[PDB]
Image: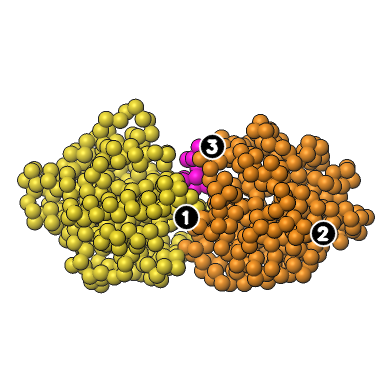
Chain colours: A yellow, B orange
Amino acid sequence: GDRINTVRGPITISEAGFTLTHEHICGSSAGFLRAWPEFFGSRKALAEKAVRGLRRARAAGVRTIVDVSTFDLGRDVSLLAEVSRAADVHIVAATGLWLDPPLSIRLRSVEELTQFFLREIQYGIEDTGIRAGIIKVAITGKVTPFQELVLRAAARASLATGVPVITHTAASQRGGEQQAAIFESEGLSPSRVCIGHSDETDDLSYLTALAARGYLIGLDRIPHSAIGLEDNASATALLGSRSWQTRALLIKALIDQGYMKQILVSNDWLFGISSYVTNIMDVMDSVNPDGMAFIPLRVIPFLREKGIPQETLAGITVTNPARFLSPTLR
Amino acid sequence: GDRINTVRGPITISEAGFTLTHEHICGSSAGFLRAWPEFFGSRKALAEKAVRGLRRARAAGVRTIVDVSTFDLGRDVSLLAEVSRAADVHIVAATGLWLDPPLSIRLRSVEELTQFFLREIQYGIEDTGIRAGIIKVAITGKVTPFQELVLRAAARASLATGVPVITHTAASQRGGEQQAAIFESEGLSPSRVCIGHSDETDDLSYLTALAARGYLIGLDRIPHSAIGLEDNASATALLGSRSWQTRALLIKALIDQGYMKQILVSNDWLFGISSYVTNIMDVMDSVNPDGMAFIPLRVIPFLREKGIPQETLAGITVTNPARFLSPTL
Ligand SMILES: C[As](C)(=O)[O-]
Ligand SMILES: [Zn+2]
Ligand SMILES: [Zn+2]
Ligand SMILES: [Zn+2]
Ligand SMILES: [Zn+2]
């Protein structure tokens, strides 16, 4: 209603403050952090880096992050709770599915996946009593048959709980349209849906069209634009070629179209990553040493220079996430 | 050298007794049992079912099972420890990889995979201090590039620690020769390798030639048969269309060729399954109500009736697994 579930329990809407709506403590795989913590140096080393990173974001104004790591991204909510306490930053946990479901998940029906997402929202994650405050889904291309199952289960869990849905759009193929078609077929309100990674395209008319329909637009990979690395071929399939200012101008463009209320902004950062080639974390930290503080330290000042008023920036970073996350069936 | 790691700690090879070398408490995926236990009704219900089944096996003479569930098969070694203790049956845990590695595993180098396998053998699984006593690997058809990394890491781990390797092939497949090539290229002794699910075909030429090279032959899916379940595409794809007697006759055939010392026998049973279609566990329990007791209760006397001496059967069910499991550098 007016309360959001975090890994430290419920908080009221006003407590959320400046919120980054798409982040990760660790990008991994189910079971991996507990089976092979030394991959990250140690669990303690990962925890400590994440606490410093969160404290840095906090000093830059951030009060809440949404960790949209799912089961199959190796989400460890006990780790989230630990670093949230030590850094005094709220963390909202996620249910849903990313792009690496194991057999025990890939073989499930839409009704089974609905029950899974529901248990993580209504009951808790694993045996921790920590409840998810968001549902995350991922698609590739035009949306695969299994991904459509996931999208429908997500819609149904959202409809039962009021908790919103956030998507990973991995396509050069105006990937939102097919997502929206499926969500709407299920009776889900666009206002419960963020179409994420929308800063991956320059297709403004496409983004504006979604915004006009009531979808939230996730401009949430701003620092992955990067710059400089064409020597590592596996650094263009995780970063990019456009500049971060180019991505950030999409924020101004949507504002100018009159859809400031539809925008969510984030870094899609993390403090550890195992679901990619070894040492990619070091490359990422080199390119973006600001980490999760990139949005408040770089993008916000950049927008202010481009004439975006304080109140509009506060609306995007405080009010929109608050309205989005607050569980709602209207 | 004479001590085997179990989920309750070290045991002497004399204490292992009648050993089933290829079994599962639960066939699942990494993290799945702890994220969604109510898929199995509850964790408590799964544990209770495993203990009832293990106790029936114990009654039938079974003293040790080897749970060859890997990380990616959802191995929960805390569950293994709980049901081992309650059933009072030794359970040897596994490291290695099966057919569902996640990205964080699929993208690793042969050196990294070797370190992971060594961790689970030398240090312990997760934070439990429970050490693996066997390395499990799996292939599908022609060994994929990634599967070849897994096989080489398994060989390197086995050579460093002396614990044996056990392999999977898919339903009705014959990949031992492919696997053996890679293992031997790493300098691994065939006596440290069990070519598993070798009862999937009746290619006796294939079986005897591996045996002649010193490989253990895993005739380990004996009760798996979908005879009478022809309308069920999922069951038949899983269990196959060959009778348990047909599978069991391969044990006799290899004995008759003089290879009794190379034979390992098991059920490849499990008490919960999430890594396949829903409610497949109920179908399998209907097929084989004996569960893991199927080998001592049905296969052993079947072979007795075919004239195999009791001492040969004891050699296969006790001595062979002991020689196999005992760490040898
Ligand atoms: C769990 As199996 C059928 O790969 O031995
Ligand atoms: Zn994403
Ligand atoms: Zn992400
Ligand atoms: Zn197998
Ligand atoms: Zn098996």
What's drawn in magenta, residue-wise?
A: B97-109
Q: Amino acid at mark 3?
A: Val
Q: Which label sits on residue B110?
A: 3
- The chain identifier of the residue carrying mark 3 reads B
Q: Secondary structure at mark 2?
A: helix
- The quarter of the picture where residue A311 lies is bottom left
Q: Is residue A298 left or right of residue B9?
A: left
Q: Which residue is mark 1?
A: A34
- The chain identifier of the residue carrying mark 1 reads A
Which is closer to the viewer, label 3 or label 2? 3
Q: Position of residue B315 (x, y in %)?
A: 84, 53
Using a 10 Å C-alpha cutoff, classify the residue at mark 3 as few (fewer than 14 neighbours), some (14 to 19) or many (20 or more): some
Please tell me which residue is depicted at 9% across the width and 47% down the height of the picture. Answer: A304
Tell me how far mark 3 sits from mark 2, CA to CA: 40 Å
Q: Amino acid at mark 1?
A: Arg
Which is closer to the viewer, label 1 or label 2? 1
Using a 10 Å C-alpha cutoff, classify the residue at mark 1 as few (fewer than 14 neighbours), some (14 to 19) or many (20 or more): some
Q: Position of residue B169 (x, y in %)?
A: 67, 45
Q: Is residue B224 above or below residue B198?
A: below
Q: Which residue is mark 2?
A: B299
- The chain identifier of the residue carrying mark 2 reads B
Position of the N terminus of chain A, as image quadrant, is bottom left
Q: Position of residue B98 (x, y in %)?
A: 59, 48
Q: Secondary structure at mark 3?
A: helix
Please tell me which residue is depicted at 78% across the width and 36% down the height of the picture. Answer: B213
Tell me how far mark 3 sits from mark 1, CA to CA: 21 Å
